[PDB]
Amino acid sequence: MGRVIRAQRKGAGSVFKAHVKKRKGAAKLRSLDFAERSGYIRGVVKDIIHDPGRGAPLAVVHFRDPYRYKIRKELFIAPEGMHTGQFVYCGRKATLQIGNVMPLSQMPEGTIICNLEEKTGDRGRLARTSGNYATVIAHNQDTKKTRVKLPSGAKKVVPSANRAMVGIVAGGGRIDKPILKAGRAYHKYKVKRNSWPKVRGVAMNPVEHPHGGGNHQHIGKASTVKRGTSAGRKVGLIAARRTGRIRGGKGDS
RNA sequence: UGCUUGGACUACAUAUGGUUGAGGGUUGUA
RNA sequence: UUAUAUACAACCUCAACUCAUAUGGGACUACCCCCUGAAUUUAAGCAUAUUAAUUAGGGGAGGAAAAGAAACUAACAAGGAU
RNA sequence: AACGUACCUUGAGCAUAUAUGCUGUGACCCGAAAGAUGGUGAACUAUACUUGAUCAGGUUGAAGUCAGGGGAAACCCUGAUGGAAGACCGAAACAGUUCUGACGUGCAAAUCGAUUGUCAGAAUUGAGUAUAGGGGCGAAAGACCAAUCGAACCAUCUAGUAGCUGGUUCCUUCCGAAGUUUCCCUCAGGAUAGCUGGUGCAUUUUAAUAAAUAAUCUUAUCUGGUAAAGCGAAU
RNA sequence: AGAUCAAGGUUAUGAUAUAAAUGUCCCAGUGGGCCACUUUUGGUAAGCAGAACUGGCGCUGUGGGAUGAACCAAACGUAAU
RNA sequence: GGUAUGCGUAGAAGUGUUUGGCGUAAGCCUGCAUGGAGCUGCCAUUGGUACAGAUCUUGGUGGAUAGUAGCAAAUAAUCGAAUGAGAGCCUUGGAGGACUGAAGUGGAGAAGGGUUUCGUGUGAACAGUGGUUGAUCACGAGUUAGUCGGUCCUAAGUUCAAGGCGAAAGCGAAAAUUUUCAAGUAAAACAUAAUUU
RNA sequence: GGCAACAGGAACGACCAUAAAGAAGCCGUCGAGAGAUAUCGGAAGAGUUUUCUUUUCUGUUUUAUAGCCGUACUACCAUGGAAGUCUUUCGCAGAGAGAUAUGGUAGAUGGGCUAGAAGAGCAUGACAUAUACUGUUGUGUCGAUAUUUUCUCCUCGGACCUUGAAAAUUUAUGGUGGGGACACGCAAACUUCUCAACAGGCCGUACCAAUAUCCGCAGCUGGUCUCCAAGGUGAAGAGUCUCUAGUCGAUAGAAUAAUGUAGGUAAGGGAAGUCGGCAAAUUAGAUCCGUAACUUCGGGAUAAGGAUUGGCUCUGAAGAUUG
RNA sequence: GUCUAAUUAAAACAAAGCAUUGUGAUGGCCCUAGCGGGUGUUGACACAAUGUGAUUUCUGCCCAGUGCUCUGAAUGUCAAAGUGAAGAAAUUCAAGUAAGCGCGGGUCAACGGCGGGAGUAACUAUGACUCUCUUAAGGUAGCCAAAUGCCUCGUCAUCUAAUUAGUGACGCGCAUGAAUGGAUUAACGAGAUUCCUACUGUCCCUAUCUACUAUCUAGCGAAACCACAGCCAAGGGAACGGGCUUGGAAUAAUUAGCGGGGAAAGAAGACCCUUUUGAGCUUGACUCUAAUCUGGCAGUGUAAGGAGACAUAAGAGGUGUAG
RNA sequence: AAAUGGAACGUGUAUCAUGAUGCAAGCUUCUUGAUCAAAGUAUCACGAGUACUCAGGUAUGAUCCAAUUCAAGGACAUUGCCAGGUAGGGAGUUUGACUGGGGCGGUACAUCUCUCAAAUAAUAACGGAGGUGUCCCAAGGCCAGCUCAGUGCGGACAGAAACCACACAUAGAGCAAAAGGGCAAAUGCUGACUUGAUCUCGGUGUUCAGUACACACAGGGACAGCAAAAGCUCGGCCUAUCGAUCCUUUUGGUUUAAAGAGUUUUUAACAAGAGGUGUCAGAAAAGUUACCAUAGGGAUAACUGGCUUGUGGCGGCCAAGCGUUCAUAGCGACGUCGCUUUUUGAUCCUUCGAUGUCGGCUCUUCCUAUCAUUGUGAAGCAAAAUUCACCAAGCGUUGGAUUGUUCACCCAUGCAAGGGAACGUGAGCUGGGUUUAGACCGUCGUGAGACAGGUUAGUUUUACCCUACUAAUGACAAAACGUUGUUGCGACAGCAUUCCUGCGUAGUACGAGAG
């Protein structure tokens, strides 16, 4: 037997639950309702806020509700260069300037987008973190399927009616400065989750880790596991195609 | 109407009945 | 009378009610009915087997319960619910 | 006709009491480390949340700023200001380095004393919560999860099993051993024969008011290749 | 190789007989042995290791060897001589 | 179970004992002592049937030592008086010399405690010395709220209409679907209206 | 009403809607006041008198709630137009998107007055009354210096791949429709003004909070969250000493052997001791000088190595209001 | 910074930095009996899995083995189901045969690995060179008697009066070596080690003063342990006696010490061996298993086209002597 | 679940010669404002109260059609059931015995031969030398014929060369193989012919329990082979060359059964073989634990004590010698004989319900196997210096650098620096070495983890008992006789002093001088 390993103990909850307390409330696009489906709609952007845990600022845009008398406040992923008191024009007949949202059909190839929709109407899934964006690389008038290029480089074929906000998302690129200390990684993660100080599993005892155990810190078995290899064995370099120093041909084609 | 002190009632699930009903369910007469 | 332009009357399906009247949820544990189900042990080791179709069970009843009036036995000179 | 045999050769059994033995059951008594079924714990400690409170005094002197001074410029040189930092010495606190000091039937089931480590942070703490046992939590020691942890605690299964240890309670009278053989996942145990006691029974001119057995010598007769002898017999 | 008759002297070494013969209960325990003469193998030796024979100790007291599991005498009901 | 026409408050069992014997022994009889109500011999048949051991069980007791180890951290008390059977205490009161030394050996609260609180008494026990004193013992008392708190709100979380699931019990349930699954309004007709999952 | 900032005794919430308050961490921070402590003055009473000391000491206080004045501070308003740039902070903050100026508005958390305030009451100190529940005299007054030795208010900052609760409850304003709404008045006013009646239930409330009330089997040197906080010397909530409160309770007497546990000193030598300088010893605060290898240029560094310091009597420098 | 509360605070963990891995949500890692969830209020500057461990300077070669992946050109293995055939049937046979495996490609900042012998330079020595045998590649930059070197107290220099220690070099390195990271590295360390000053009772070599004990007293008062006990030498014995045997000797009751014995007390030996006793851990152990992937069947429908013109409407072929 | 899919007027691009045709297309983009709740419109209520106060409803505004809330997939995924692969993530369990501890080795685990084995037979050790797990259609059977190792003399090419050839030739040859027996008109060699290497029933020998396999043997029955016959043959000239149950299998009856009855398939039964257990009287089975555990063991190691001596250490006999000459002043080759047991082992006697396991520090005493000192002897002894030997344990036998070590070597002292005993001495200390748990390297392992390799950090308890010892008081009685004091005596026990140097002696003796 063993102990249940640490890789297995995160899917269960308690001390590997997210710390979602002061989070400002799930940034999404507005719902693809009617105004975005025939014309457009205008709302100002009242504040920029930093969600505690996030990496990119969020925008508190609020529009008018068209069928009720309410002002409907909305959190958006802020594209870069969005002051307060800007008018954002979310809809189909809007024009190309940042960060209006408009379906992929209207905006022309070569543009760069963010907070893109994956399935047509689902409020904003792809390319949402700071500094990232997705270029619209091509179109098709046959069955309306637009190729975008996502931040991994993998070129997806989304359909051509799902909304997206034009412009590269504000707050980048922040991964370029060293954290430098361990009490800046303590602070980085105390509002995200308990991916702790992560101990190396080669230094545990042979009960709690596959890699762990010996008289020397060493693996001995291979660190590339199979894909289907049955937690808590699937540990280390899962399902690895190649390993070692990649040279040149990282290129995603 | 304001307060006090006493009483009576108000749980869910269900069966038959009662009462108001709902439906581009199914027809009928206007 | 059904462009979802009103009403009527039925029926079906379905609601709601501090509606009128009713049941239901005990808990006991020796026996009883249905489940669910080990390992100690034994094998002079041990893995099927054994424990045991049993401890732990674990829901449901009665004064008993369950059963029960042959889709039964038998091969005879034939028997006859449980 | 031959071989076979748990069979027959004119019935001896059935019931029962007791003693001994062999086997099944708690099995003469007490004794495991363990396995399982269902429960109870985060009042201690680990971690995470939510909400509160806490840390004398100094020491250093980042950026930013201000004025002089040198320069064709580039830009530099000096004096202040300023008050940064998982920076410094240290109090409270939190920790526990050395003395291998005290103590060691304690003051204490981990404390006492001087000496040390940190001290504004990956800080220390309360309260409410959250995670439960082949599970949790872990800046990782198999650490901690109520003085319990290379698997908590509790009750039961259960009087688990034990080829091993310890014991096994009156007195006289009679007889009186074995440590060997064969087999065994057998070598601290069994089975198995030898040795033992009991209880009979049959009976003798070696049994009851021998012209016949049996075990040391003699006789007669077989066998033997050791002591001695031998290499002027073989090898 | 047998089945019945005929003849056969004095029963065919010695000394022994605490009785022998035979079943059952293969009933209890035991299945660690040690010591010694002579024989003997391994070891250099060993109060070591392993066998053959007989006797002992184990189970056994008493007399002797000052002393002692096995040596030498001797085996043990209570007493006198 | 039968028997001894047994023994017994005129003294049963038991217990003690320099009572006296019997037995090879296990044992047994008997006198006296104490005791105060039951008991034995024999023939059967039986049993929870005999102890020196088991680091045996349970209770008691010895030596040590019946008074030995010891009652040594937190600087420290001393006078005289009153008590009182008895005073090194704390018993008290006056002098008193000292300690803590405001990050106290100070004054109050949280958790915890549960009457320890406070008067009047007081013997034993307890207070590892004593004790007249006591957080002890005995007996009487004592906690007063519109304003201080709870109560009210929601946090993490408990997750909780069964739509669901499971043989059930029940459920590592940020449900994500459960007709109105609504929280609703002095609101008109011909299910009050944009509305709230 | 006021040009305006806004102002007054009230002056269509019944909804829909929007905004705000509730609603806040951390570290530092100019300034305001409180509280304390502190000198020098009045008073009133104690202390001390070897000798000397106009001494050395205590005491002098004003709760909520209100009324009014009220000004610092920050930001707005009006007139106005700024380079020869001026304003201003410890700190670099501002200004043609209106500076400096002159006048004003807002906020007052800040105090000063006066109600409370019966010489409130209190405190002190005289008396006086066998004495009880006592009658009574007289005081209570000036200035000033100091620290987050401590709270509170205000200001501006700082760090951050950290950016620092939700709801109850409250309030304002905006809105359509609806109500109030005569002028010869009678009035009204969930009136968001003033005044008056009445009521406010349930439950906790003693005491300890630990060298003796708690947990550790105990009157156990351990443990167990907070609040208040004096004088001295000093950088200091340090260490020694003391004031207010609090204790002398740790079984007591005699005596001072050996070995000890704890603390001192030791000639000469100075690590020879020892596994090893373990243990001890040395140095240490402050001012001034001065400082090496190496370096990630930041440090090293308090490197090293030196000098100074008491007491007494003097001199010089640093400020404030008035000129 | 952090850990083994109650023997180890360290060089171990962590850490920033570096790098490899998976994943575009019908997803990746995870939990769940089942339903459903966690990351996730998430979206490649993100979540998840590892290794290395700041900086600097670097990171050689090997894809034979084991893994891991592949868009893998897939006749060799080959499940059930469906399929054909033989039989009266059970049944037996044959084709076909998915994923894996087999074959094949890629990867080592995946697990790991990283050679021999011979001959030679006008003195010996050494071998730049040469032969040659093997292998996947033969250990490259580098460092080193290393906390890593057996031999070893290696050899040389230094530090010393003397050094199995330290240091610095040398390198046929039993058995160094490059993110199993190599060589360095300033600052920092209750870390390991060496030496020089300073300083001393550590020592030569002990002495004395203090306090509290112990001591004696009054009061109070345990425990451990205990076969019976406690004078030796020698002998013999189960081979180290208080007891036996032979001597030596042998006199009460006691106080403070002491640490020779009692093979002294604790404690059914922590090592070791046995037990057909276990438990924790591993893994190409035997045998199972969750989850996973893969095939089949079920749910499971309506349309067209191509390959099947099958069962079928209907059509057509015939030359040996002779005739 | 808010505006889905149509169509329609609307305006424009565009075409067709004012049409139709296909498309755009019906309103919000300079600005941090604002919007909810119908205006208008028409027709009816078109009136009520009564011009007078006061009024609805519908569409329109805001076009009609058809519902599928809308999307994205979609007869796939998901799910049910089966099947294949995968799977130390998890589970259960195993991981031989023997053995001069265990492990490693090895096979002494089944079996055979000679020896041990001590004259029946039996007999043991991880005693000695070997063997076996096969081989053979002839190497089995049988009848006949011939004789082998070798040596000797001869013969063209002919030595060792072959091959022919005559005499000798007791097995010195051969007999599948180990060893032992055995065999000469064979059991050997060659030739003939062969299948008895078959079928059946019991019994005996061995092993022995006096059980089974297996091998062998003596027979009965049957069928055969060779041989003229007698006879011989039931494998191998004899002693090794082998394997249960269960299951699978095949061959055999012209088989028995399937239990309601018939026939056929099938299955089973019975008999004889086969498939194999080598750990061979026969489980189906990998490691590790320094994180550990229990039952035990002195049946069993590490540790003291005992016994033992290859090793350690050791002194006499005899002299080949060396010693210039000279054997023995001093040594002494090859021999030979004894002595000690602290190491090294050897064993496994004692202890595993525990004897604290290295050293050092401290402190005692004892032993001589004499280093120095006292007393002497000898010398290849002139003096000095030294060497040999005797009586001798009285007094000594040091300070330090490195290392945990003991011996160790080195500096220094010294006219001159012996060796040992309770493996002396841990409730004496210490804790440096080894030696639990932490951690790091190097090697080894796939790994857990290992290492008679290195490094670091690692809890050292109790005396108050008896005794011994050290000091301190000390009675009753007893007594060659009271109570008390004073002054003594010694039996007995202890026993302690020690070496060094300087000046004289004297530059003397001695020597040639140097000394």
Image: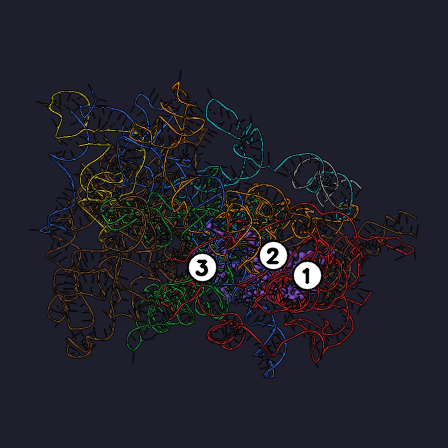
Chain colours: A purple, C cyan, D blue, E yellow, F orange, G red, H green, I brown
Marks 1 and 3, how far apart in space?
A: 54 Å
Residue E45 coordinates in the image, percent (x, y): 22, 51
In the drawing, does residue H1 fall left or right of residue G319? left
Q: Amino acid at mark 2?
A: Val
Local SS, label 1: strand
Residue A198 coordinates in the image, percent (x, y): 52, 59
Q: Amino acid at mark 1?
A: Val
In this view, the residue in front, D229 or F126, is F126
| Numbered disc total | 3
Task: Please name the residue shown 43% across and 59% down the image.
Answer: A216
- Residue that label 2 marks: A20
Marks 2 and 3, how far apart in space?
A: 37 Å
In this view, the residue in front, G120 or A213, is G120
Q: Are marks 2 and 3 in contact (CB under 8 Å)?
A: no
Marks 2 and 1, how far apart in space?
A: 22 Å
In this view, the residue in front, C20 or I44, is C20
Q: Which mark is residue A61?
A: 1
The answer to whether marks 1 and 3 sit on the same chain is yes
Q: Chain of mark 3?
A: A
Q: Chain of mark 2?
A: A
The answer to whether marks 2 and 3 sit on the same chain is yes
In the drawing, does residue D140 fall left or right of residue F186? left
Local SS, label 3: loop
Task: Please name the residue shown 67% across and 65% down the image.
Answer: A83
Q: Quadrant of the C terminus of chain A?
A: bottom right
**Earlier-in-chain disc, 2 versus 1:** 2
Q: Amino acid at mark 3?
A: Gln
The answer to whether residue A108 of the structure is visible from this angle is: yes
Q: Which mark is residue A217?
A: 3
Local SS, label 2: loop
